[PDB]
Amino acid sequence: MAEVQLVESGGGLVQAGDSLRLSATASGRTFSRAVMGWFRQAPGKEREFVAAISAAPGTAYYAFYADSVRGRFSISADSAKNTVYLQMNSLKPEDTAVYYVAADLKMQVAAYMNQRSVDYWGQGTQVTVSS
């Protein structure tokens, strides 16, 4: 498949209870009407799905959240700005991980994403939550 360079930003050291926003864009070649998602991974841990997003009619989007982040995280996107976002609220030490943006080109709508079906990964951005 064609080369695509996804780049995550926003990682940092925060405290339990804080909010932190992550963003992701492509460097050069990008997508249009792709199902985008966030995953996270601590060393030795399995890569975990976090949230997914895909375009709906007009300026609306479909979203889907893992149970681990329901009520706390929100995924959004800006078409013109070629960016996808993950607003993390009420962070806790168990959210500590490297967060990766993902694209799965077979999927048509936002839903649960299997890490093994992902076509493109970013390089990841470390999020560290101290108690």
Image (spheres, rainbow, N blue to C red):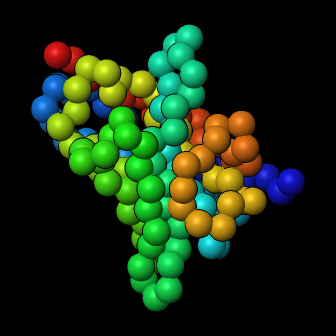
**Residue 42 drawn at (x, y percent):** 48, 19
Place of residue 47 in the rendered image (x, y in percent of width and height, measured from the top left) = 57, 28
Judge left or right: residue 45 versus residue 66. right
Instruction: Residue at the far right: name it.
Output: 1
Residue placed most toward the observer, 100 or 64: 64
Point 49% across, 54% down: residue = 52
Where does the C terminus fall, quadrant-wise?
top left
Q: Residue at x 55, y 49 (%)?
A: 112
Q: Is residue 30 above or below residue 3?
A: below
Residue at the bottom extreme, as displayed: 58
As drawn, which residue projects farthest toward the left?
17
In front: 54, or 4? Answer: 54
Does the image show residue 123? yes
Quadrant (top left, top right, bottom left, bottom right) of the N terminus: bottom right
The percent position of residue 41, horizontal first and vertical second, equals 50, 25
Q: Where does residue 125 sit, x and y in percent of width and height? A: 46, 34
The residue that appears at 44% across and 62% down in the rendered structure is 63
* Relative side of 103 to 55, left or right: right
User: Residue at image x 59%, y 36%?
Assistant: 123
